[PDB]
Image (cartoon, rainbow, N blue to C red):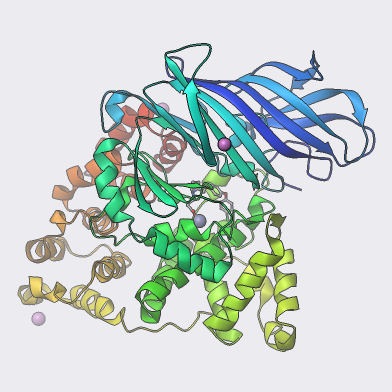
Amino acid sequence: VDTCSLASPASVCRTKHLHLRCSVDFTRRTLTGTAALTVQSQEDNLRSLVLDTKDLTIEKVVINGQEVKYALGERQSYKGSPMEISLPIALSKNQEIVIEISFETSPKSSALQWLTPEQTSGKEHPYLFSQCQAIHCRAILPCQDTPSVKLTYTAEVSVPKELVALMSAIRDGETPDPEDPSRKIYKFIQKVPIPCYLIALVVGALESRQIGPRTLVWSEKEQVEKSAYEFSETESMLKIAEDLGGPYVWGQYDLLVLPPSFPYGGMENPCLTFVTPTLLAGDKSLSNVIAHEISHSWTGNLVTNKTWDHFWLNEGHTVYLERHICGRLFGEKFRHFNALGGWGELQNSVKTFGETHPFTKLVVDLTDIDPDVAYSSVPYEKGFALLFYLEQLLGGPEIFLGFLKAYVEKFSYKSITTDDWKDFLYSYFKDKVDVLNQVDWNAWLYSPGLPPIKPNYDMTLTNACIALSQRWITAKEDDLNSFNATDLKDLSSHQLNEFLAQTLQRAPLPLGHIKRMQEVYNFNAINNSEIRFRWLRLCIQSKWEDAIPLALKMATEQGRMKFTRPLFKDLAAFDKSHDQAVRTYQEHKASMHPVTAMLVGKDLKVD
Ligand SMILES: O=C([O-])CCCN1CCC[C@H]1COc1ccc(Oc2ccc(Cl)cc2)cc1
Ligand SMILES: [Yb+3]
Ligand SMILES: [Yb+3]
Ligand SMILES: [Yb+3]
Ligand SMILES: [Zn+2]
């Protein structure tokens, strides 16, 4: 049972295919058209079915060339409104029919962000992008909005002719629009069955540059050169991922660099990964995000969580593969550094929520919880922690990677639960079951807080970050003179970041220490978004007023929630910046991503 969906479940009927024909109307901020769903009955004598919708205007529903009865139920908050459709003829088990629904989105669609020309790089054209995960696909089109159902799709999208449409699918050509020659129709085919949260659409003034034998980078013209360089490791990461996961089945692996308001680091849309422009550090240092999105081509897109309660299956395995990719590229010591880093991020999350909070459980219960509100690092890092602990328990990285590849093979094209996973783990490691029985499963899977066991981490690359962080934390005023730019001499960008992360865990520090840190390390000059984020949080939590305009600027000039949410929260907790934060949020709210606006509003206790 998917408690986040109001639609008929997979045991009742299953969508096999979507044919989407729609037109993107920038004047009205609406997507209008028809979603033709090929639906297969799973029951005898099926006479109706229910679809998810959210802020959709339904014009009509046609089956067998005739309009049929349908009814929209009462809105159920963030879940939207159920759509019951009366079938004209009862279906037997396995019988398929095509249901064509004429619809229109709301400008307020929580799936979509509509951007004015001024919010783009070029300033001459508007831009649209979607984000369906977890349950926003219903805010674009009527569907069974559950990852328990997988469907193929085709789409024809009409857009102003100077713009380009892209989707999570293979590009299938373009033509002038036969009805309106000011428009183009872009065609798309996704022949691999996918859960509907992986349907994605972007429309804007996009250009492309090839960076590998199966990868183009797409963005507005002013970001193309920078993006091509930043993501040049992509093909070599795909080859490693294929080695670990098996064949890449999706054909193309393209990248789209979104405008700065994209709410996340990345999104693993099949054939077309979406990435934040905050990755454009200039030195490829934030490329683990690409490795992570690549990994989803197996863990998430092939093997999918059956409901959102099992989201950790998607993320833990993907972070696990991610860290293997970076370990192949840069060494096993680097994999351990990143893994130990992740544990720190897990400590932070658990401390933030509280150690008994239900969202610190690996397997969660999302009944009456908005998944956007539950979203955190917990399923990523507690899920990774579990796999890493199992790896060490069961004999090492190469043994456990044998299991990961067998897992992907086993559940490819399926949607699975934690029990499916656990069962297969026991099946695969039959000769090591006694060891498996030592694991405290009820704690790992179902209890809040930090895991019952912390894995073993090589400390080599972390030691210098910890030592430097500890010098600063234990420094008194008379020690401040001893710090100097040479302290940073032998630290990579990642170590610099971890140094700040270590220090941030003990924030606030005395204001005088922070002022000195700027004087000798000039952190204000660093444009690496991850480093800058932690440095600004450290400044604001340590009550440095000078940092207020910098923190406000970063919070608003990009919209990646990882950065924007804690920056607004920190600014609101600082009495000197509190009113500015609230005011800045209020003035920016209408032009923010709708999900980001909602969550920042909640964080700030506004509107
Ligand atoms: O590949 C990635 O992990 C990129 C980060 C994921 N981003 C990409 C755009 C969408 C977003 C994931 O969005 C979600 C995903 C899952 C959500 O629901 C849950 C939130 C927490 C839990 Cl423990 C279970 C389910 C809610 C929102
Ligand atoms: Yb074709
Ligand atoms: Yb002293
Ligand atoms: Yb108010
Ligand atoms: Zn992920």
